[PDB]
Amino acid sequence: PKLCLVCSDEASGCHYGVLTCGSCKVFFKRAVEGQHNYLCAGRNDCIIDKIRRKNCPACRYRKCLQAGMNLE
Amino acid sequence: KLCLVCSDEASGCHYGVLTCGSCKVFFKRAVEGQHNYLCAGRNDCIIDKIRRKNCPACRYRKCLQAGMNL
DNA sequence: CCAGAACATCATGTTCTG
DNA sequence: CCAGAACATGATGTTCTG
Ligand SMILES: [Zn+2]
Ligand SMILES: [Zn+2]
Ligand SMILES: [Zn+2]
Ligand SMILES: [Zn+2]
């Protein structure tokens, strides 16, 4: 098996340049195309795992960027 | 005038406390649903009009600290 | 005016299609 | 295999109903 570089769930494949799970793949594509602006309610360092990833879009988006996801 | 939980514009006195509509229904569903809420932070999230949706654990906790019940 | 239900929209995740 | 669209669903918020 292989892990999502963003949320540590089971990766489904290489998406947007990075190993990710399906949910993170479509989250990113949705985050980079739409207007959302996200606000972190903690300290910009929220725990993004399978359980908590939808708590903080802001921190999930940032982790997406830091892993190097991009549309091409 | 301001929701004690999220500082959004309150609507009336709900469950003991001046809160907004969204907080009223969140609180009732919280208590009467008993979901496993988990904070992604340190159990001290900021809860305002936007951030209240981020962390229902902290939101439900702040409701309690405000005095909401029944 | 307020509680509870009903409705409407959000946000997310799986599945399908190209 | 991967991207983009379509579908499915549970959480949130507003409106109606008692
Ligand atoms: Zn992921
Ligand atoms: Zn965060
Ligand atoms: Zn509120
Ligand atoms: Zn929290």
Image: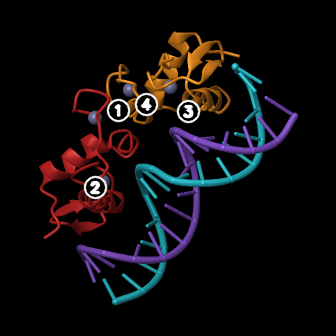
Chain colours: A red, B orange, C cyan, D purple
Identify the chain of the residue marked 1, using the numbered disc in the image: B
Q: Are marks 4 and 3 on the same chain?
A: yes
Residue matched to label 1 = B40
Q: Which mark is residue B61?
A: none
Residue A55 percent location from the top left of the image: 38, 39
Q: Are marks 4 and 2 in contact (CB under 8 Å)?
A: no
- Which mark lies nearer to you, 2 or 3? 3
Q: Are marks 4 and 3 in contact (CB under 8 Å)?
A: yes
> Left of A56 or right of it: where is A69?
left
Residue matched to label 2 = A31
Q: Which mark is residue B52?
A: 4
Q: Are marks 1 and 4 in contact (CB under 8 Å)?
A: no
Identify the chain of the residue marked 4, using the numbered disc in the image: B
Identify the chain of the residue marked 3, using the numbered disc in the image: B
Q: Are marks 4 and 2 on the same chain?
A: no
Position above or below: B36 against D11? above
Q: Is label 1's Cβ within 8 Å of ligand 2?
A: yes
Q: Quadrant of ligand 2?
A: top left
Residue matched to label 3 = B22
Q: CA distance from mark 3 to mark 1?
A: 21 Å
Q: CA distance from mark 1 to mark 4?
A: 13 Å
Residue kind at label 3, given as amino acid type: Ser
Residue kind at label 4, given as amino acid type: Arg
Residue D18: name its quadrant.
top right
Which residue: 12% across, 56% down?
A68
In this rendered view, identify the residue nearer to me: B22 or B45. B22
Q: Are marks 1 and 4 on the same chain?
A: yes
